[PDB]
Image (tube, chains in turn orange, green):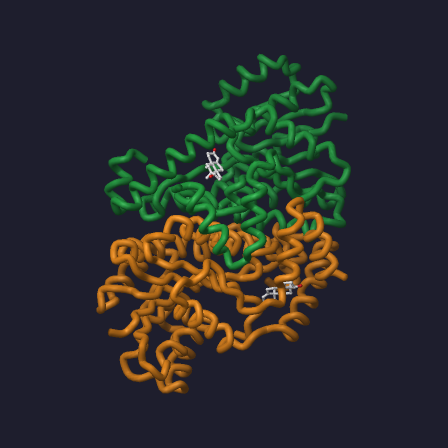
Length: 278
Length: 278
Ligand SMILES: C[C@]12CC[C@H]3[C@@H](CCC4=CC(=O)CC[C@@]43C)[C@@H]1CC[C@@H]2O
Ligand SMILES: C[C@]12CC[C@H]3[C@@H](CCC4=CC(=O)CC[C@@]43C)[C@@H]1CC[C@@H]2O
């Protein structure tokens, strides 16, 4: 039978491209449940699916809001096969700005969607995998989950949290036959100045501008095509003994090694301040 | 004048012992605001304060619930000096058990207290430090924030999140004169089987027992006295150029280095499964 895949956050970006890559696979090996918070956003997904000639029935959309455990359970019940071979936890939110300028609701939302929503997915689908002794779980990671980035304090908190969540589960899941992997992505092709200025000091504001200018230059130079990133997920899926982490690029490994080599954090803080700010 | 210190989570453990260490310092250098979620739990703190003969006025208690930004702001207004020289973000919750056995509320609470509550403290007190160009922020960390531990999935998610939060802020704060440091603690001297069994499978349940037996043995062998741990906070406070991280012990550095040296995570997962389970 087909490998049943359920992917969260398929309205755009990595989840959209992964969903159509799998559904359009020439071997027709996969049945994909592409889940979205709001079905009103499914148009780009269906435009992409048609462009790759996904066979009828290879791709289905479900509404799934990872903030709501009832929505998670209702989507699980919509899997007609009664099993999920591959779960891809990809839904996520970004949050950029001076820490004191971020709304309390926005902070709590990033954590609820990125972290608690992944926990909700894992609590809903892991038990069936553990009892069957098979299943693959892929989690969309970021280089921001491996090293702290200025003005991404809460985003990095949430991506570092997925690292701890997944590494902790991987230690237990080792002998269960259930494989969990993080796909560590760099940049991928996919408030107003006035309000930020009102909630922070002028120096922090100026540094935010510098960060934004630097970020745009790196994105322009180094963002990867979503097709190349989606193929790393497929590589992890086909591995007989998948590792805990896959990297979409080796570009940030040097910064990572410097980080990991000086546990006091001094070398990394100095190097990243220089890298972003000059 | 005195160095004004505000510490969260002083009802027991590290925060209680730190508060009385600082308030009883022979030099009388510190004025300590020991904050607690519920003032009904302040008895051990006052028993400890009297035992160390903390001078009258060296220690004051404030009610502060880090889940509530109004409580954070009301406590900030109670600092009569109108400034905080040292902020110690220590309030935290643990959560242990099979992931699928944890209540959704309990998960969301660990994240709200440990992560969003620290963000609330930083948003409330950082701006004044940045404008003055001085201030120390100490955050209670854990070895569980540096490496994933089985059956601590959500606890480790939350402690890994503080790593990302603090490292991201430290990159920005470098030139502001505001110093942020994590104090990485190992074990420190400080649901029912039936309900866990009903929410998980028998194999996971057996592994939980093994984890608990192992954890108790390590705690018995390696837990540090809270006095020794509190003194690491003082060491970070007195450093002219404090590093991002301080370690209370070097016992877990080897596991950490192995972790950091194999970015795929394979060596760490295998080593920690063997370390916990045999
Ligand atoms: C900060 C940074 C440039 C901006 C990058 C960041 C990695 C992650 C990232 C993803 C994006 O989509 C926007 C650009 C950013 C935010 C990079 C890591 C090192 C580099 O200097
Ligand atoms: C899991 C472990 C034993 C139990 C330790 C853990 C570090 C943190 C910790 C703190 C505690 O208070 C309980 C014991 C635990 C949970 C250790 C890290 C490696 C060691 O094998």
